Image (cartoon, rainbow, N blue to C red):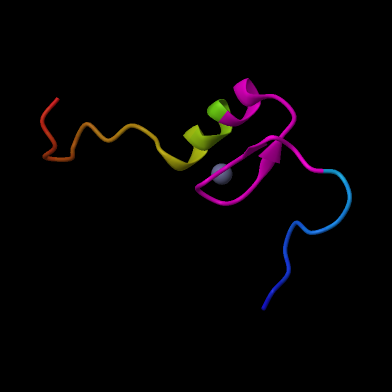
Amino acid sequence: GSSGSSGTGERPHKCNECGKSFIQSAHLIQHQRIHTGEKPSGPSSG
Ligand SMILES: [Zn+2]
């Protein structure tokens, strides 16, 4: 059991991709991007 992000000082917003955290949502909503980029090659229509 690797305890991570356990202690004092937490945020109401956390990334579901890696697990990071941010004070404001706008901060996270933007970060999550680093995980999902643009792939116009994929077959997925649209
Ligand atoms: Zn992340």
Image-based side of 18 in relation to 4, left or right: left
At horizontal 48% and vertical 33% (from top left) the residue drawn is 33
Q: Which residues are magenta?
A: 10-28
Image-based side of 38 in relation to 10, left or right: left
The image quadrant where one finds ligand 1 is top right
The residue lying furthest to the bottom in this view is 1
Q: Is residue 41 magenta?
A: no
At horizontal 39% and vertical 35% (from top left) the residue drawn is 37
Image-based side of 14 in relation to 42, left or right: right
* Camera-nearest residue between 36 and 6: 6
At horizontal 14% and vertical 37% (from top left) the residue drawn is 44
Residue 15 picture quarter: top right
Residue 18 spot, x, y in % from top left: 56, 51
Residue 23 picture quarter: top right
Residue 41 spot, x, y in % from top left: 18, 37
Vertical position of residue 36 compared to residue 6: above or below: above
Q: Is residue 21 magenta?
A: yes
The residue lying furthest to the top in this view is 26
Q: Quadrant of the C terminus?
A: top left
The residue lying furthest to the front in this view is 12
**Numbered-mark total:** 0
Residue 11 spot, x, y in % from top left: 74, 37
Q: Quadrant of the N terminus?
A: bottom right
Residue 19 spot, x, y in % from top left: 61, 50
